[PDB]
Image: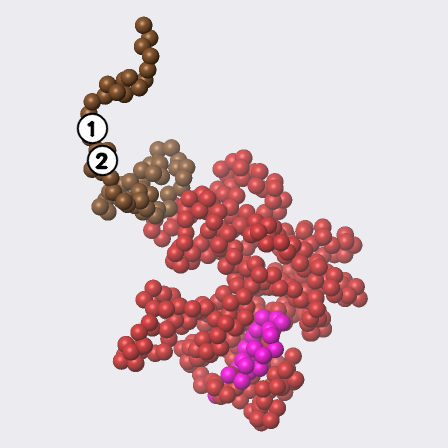
Amino acid sequence: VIPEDFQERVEQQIIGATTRLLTQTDFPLQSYEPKVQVPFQVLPGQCPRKIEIERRKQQYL
Amino acid sequence: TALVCDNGSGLCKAGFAGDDAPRAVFPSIVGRPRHQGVMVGMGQKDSYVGDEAQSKRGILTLKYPIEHGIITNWDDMEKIWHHSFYNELRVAPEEHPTLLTEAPLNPKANREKMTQIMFETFNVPAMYVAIQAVLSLYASGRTTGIVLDSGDGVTHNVPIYEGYALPHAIMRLDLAGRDLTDYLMKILTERGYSFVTTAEREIVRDIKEKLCYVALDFENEMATAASSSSLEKSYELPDGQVITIGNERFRCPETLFQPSFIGMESAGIHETTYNSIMKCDIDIRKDLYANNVLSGGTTMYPGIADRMQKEITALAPSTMKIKIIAPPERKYSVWIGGSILASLSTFQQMWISKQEYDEAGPSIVHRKCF
């Protein structure tokens, strides 16, 4: 048999996931992002732009 | 002996008459220390002015004086002149006739006010006024010319005939180096370099001086730039990040011909100049086609002479020898003209002077002057 429903699986779920709730805050996320001048479309082998943002912010924190 | 001071809105230039170059150049900015009580405690002077103001640009207040080519505040401009005379020129202003320069069509009151402030406060015995294009044509060395002038805060075209400006054919266009920097900033932001701070904006200005150039056949140039990396030119920021610019280098200059990129609707500079000469009279049109001369900072861009030559010829009837001329020093050339003009001994006979200055006084800058 192909049992009926995706929802039946979701109902069968049991637990609260790791991070979803305590992580919540009022702060806007993109607002965290430093300015940095790296283009949008880096040359392959360069870090793509979004990586630089994460790294810089993590260093700052 | 004589002094010459000039303001293409962007940067201002100070020089001794007859010299083949001005003795100092410094940028058109004033700044007051933000706590007056500290300043009076120090005795540190009223304002930083010229480049050291830039060196302190963050530590204090900064303001511009001559926006769109017009005096925004007299008191600031006189502080500029004070700094020029003492710090750059050192001379006693009382001892040396002095030349000051203005954009065209300056509202009449401003001429009188400017005269009054110079004569009464600065105490030189004699002074003269000139309209920038008129001095730049003097540097070119014609009485008979149509001038293109663009200092980074304004641009104009000016017909001048046997040494006079035919007023009605003058036009203003509010599209100048600042606007070009802002458009370039926008399009690099679309690349993702996102210059916004004053320091970065100055870096943009440097990029304009280093790497811009006009296209000829713009659509062909753009296509070839899209076709290949070979047009790329790279630059490294002061922080040591490398930035890479293609089509944008010529595309940014296009805005002069192509103001729809700015979303303003008056036709491009070539068109405006044609329409001006159309306001001038066929009697003199030929000589105007004969002497097209480029002035002020924006003319710095490579190749613009050829682009104008083509586009003017197209807009013109194909029945004259169009001749662009881009005298190498064209931005300084405005001041160079004044330097030679004041060098002319007969201009001493033109001098407006203290004795007249009592009775004939403020009005003669209208009545006697040109």
Q: Is residue B31 above or below residue B202?
A: below
The image shows residue B150 at horizontal and vertical percentages of 57, 62
In the rendered view, does A20 fall on the left or right side of B69? left
What residue appears at the point 46 percent right and 51 percent down from the top-left corner?
Answer: B185
Give the chain coloured brown. Answer: A
Helix, strand or loop under label 2: loop
The image shows residue B339 at horizontal and vertical percentages of 56, 75
Residue B330 drawn in magenta: no
Disc 2 from disc 1: Cα separation: 9 Å
The image shows residue B333 at horizontal and vertical percentages of 57, 68
Q: Is residue A43 above or below residue B148?
A: above
What residue appears at the point 56 percent right and 77 percent down from the top-left corner?
Answer: B110
What colour denotes chain B? red
Q: Chain of mark 1?
A: A
Q: Nearer the viewer, residue B331 or A36?
A: A36
Mark 1 = which residue? A16
Q: Which image quarter: residue B46? A: bottom left
Figure coloring: by chain
The image shows residue B135 at horizontal and vertical percentages of 61, 72
Q: Chain of mark 2?
A: A
Q: Is residue B254 above or below residue B353?
A: above
Q: Nearer the viewer, residue B145 or B370?
A: B370
In the rendered view, does A14 fall on the left or right side of B201? left
Q: Which residues are magenta?
A: B94-117
Report if the CB atoms under discs 2 and 1 are less than 8 Å apart.
yes
Within-10-Å neighbours for mark 2: few <14, some 14–19, many 20+: few
Amino acid of disc 2: Leu
Mark 2 = which residue? A21
